[PDB]
Amino acid sequence: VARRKPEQFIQTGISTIDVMNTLVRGQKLPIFSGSGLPANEIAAQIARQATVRPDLSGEGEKEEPFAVVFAAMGITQRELSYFIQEFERTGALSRSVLFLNKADDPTIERILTP
Amino acid sequence: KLEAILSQEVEAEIQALLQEAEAKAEAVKREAEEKAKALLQARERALEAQYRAALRRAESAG
C-alpha cells in the first residue's frame, strides 16, 4: 500500500535494457548467468555507468545524492580485487557500504549477510 | 596550316592532366587538414575526462 508505480528511468549504459525492459527505481531485474559463463565482467558495466537522467525523462534525481551499496556472498581471490578496482573507476568508496562475504569467511554467513 | 593541328592535340591533354593533378594536390591536402584537426579533437576530450575524474577522486579522498 505504501508503494506506487515508479516511472523515473536510469541510464545503465547498456542500450538493450533502457529500451526493452526499462530499468526504473524500486524494480528488480535479475541478470541470469550460467556456470562457465562470466558474471563479474557484465556486473561491473552496470556499476560505473549507473546514472539518472538529468531531464531526459522530464526530470532528474541528481539533485539528491545517488550512491550504491554492495554485498558479495561468496567470492574468490580474483573477484575480491576485481570489484574494488572498478569502484575506484566509479569514484565511489567514500559514499558506499560494502558487506563482502568471502568463501574463506564462514558458510553460514552466506545467508545471514543478505 | 598543318603545324597548327599538331599544337592542338597536345594543348588539351596538357591541361586535362594538369587540372587533374592540381585536384589530387588539393585533395590530399584537404584530408591532411581534416585529419590533424580530428587527432586534436580526440586529444581535447581526453584531457577533459582526466580532469573531471581527477577532481572527483580528490573530493572523495579528502
Image (tube, grey):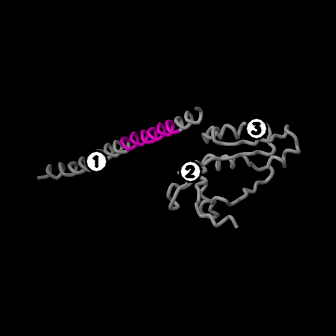
Q: Quadrant of residue A21?
A: bottom right
Residue B44 within the segment the image draws in magenta: yes
> What residue did someone put label 3 on?
A78
A56, A32: nearer the viewer: A56
Whole-number angstrom distance, CA of label 2 to CA of label 3: 34 Å
Chain of the residue under label 1: B
Residue A1: name its quadrant: bottom right
Upstream in sequence: badge 2 or badge 3 = 2
Q: Is residue A61 left or right of residue A21?
A: left
A33 to B51, vertically: above or below: below
Q: How far across and how far down the image is residue A6, in percent?
A: 62, 64
Q: Give the magenta part as a residue range.
A: B32-52
For label 1, the crowd category at 10 Å Cα-Cα, with few meaning under 14, some 14 to 19 and many 20 or more, is few
Give residue A4's position: percent from left, percent from top: 65, 66
According to the picture, the residue beneath numbered tag 2 turns out to be A64
Which residue is disc 1 drawn over? B17
* Helix, strand or loop for disc 1: helix
Q: Quadrant of the C terminus of chain B?
A: top right
Q: In this view, which residue lies farthest toward the left?
A: B1
The numbered mark 3 sits on a residue in which chain?
A
Q: Main secondary structure of the magenta part?
A: helix
Question: In the rendered view, does B19 fall on the left or right side of A94?
Answer: left
Residue at horizontal 74 percent and vertical 49 percent from the top:
A39
What amino acid type is highlighted by mark number 1?
A: Leu
* Distance in Å between CA atoms under marks 1 and 3: 66 Å
